[PDB]
Image (cartoon, rainbow over all chains, first blue to last red; front, top):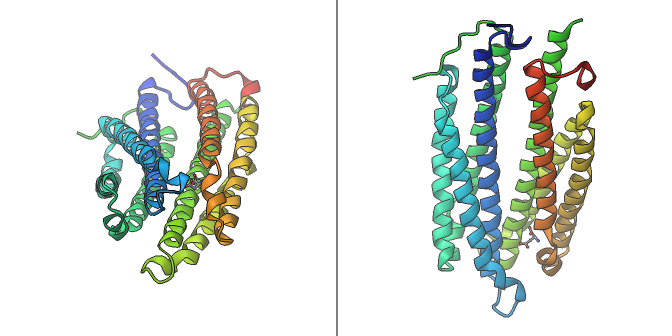
Length: 165
Length: 158
Ligand SMILES: N[C@@H](CC(=O)O)C(=O)O
């Protein structure tokens, strides 16, 4: 049977705590790629404001395509996050992330649609920054909750901890 | 002696170091976003409505970049574990390059040099840091797995 290890006397504990870390990792990747999406969008939008004769304008479409690529990758990681069952103590903060993620994700997909035809006015009018900021704060909150829970688990024994259904 | 306690402290350290690098990376991307938002206002120009925010936006980039550097200093305050030294030094080299790049961009916009701003190969510098971070994360995760599963000899952490 066990010890499995000093930190995880049963190997089930390691499965749980490792889940927890994997969920953080996939949410960190989501956030990273949403911010990369914002960067590619803004680099595209600014070039759509240029004169055609500026050679720097020529990348506007490649950059919007790169936004589409990073936003797809973000959503891939987010699905991986959601595929991993939360622990009960993480359900509330996970729902909070979900709310803010949906808002900011939707926002970014709308900006892609605006730039697709060079509609820079619709792009500027969106209050994107506030949605980004809300996601970032939700992310921070999730990370603090996760870390505190992780420390509770590894210092417990225990070796119960059961995934929420 | 005290193997469990040492494993708890070292695992906590590796997590905290990854968290600080994550914060540094996110804030450097936020700096790059804020720079681009300032550039959008400069391209609207005069009193074209959101255009008067160019300075506030550029100050917001300076703020995120200083916050990045704060987290990076926190990262450096945690001594690397032996098998993490080289990947830590790789992060240092790529961080410094990208940090300098972003300071150059700030300076370009502060002096109205939009051309130099757009011509800098910023993406390559970001990507090089991102690859350094990926290498670091791989190395850290191998060590972490070994520590928390009692598969690490004492030299690696104790
Ligand atoms: N070179 C800067 C500005 C730009 O090209 O839009 C960047 O890549 O962030």
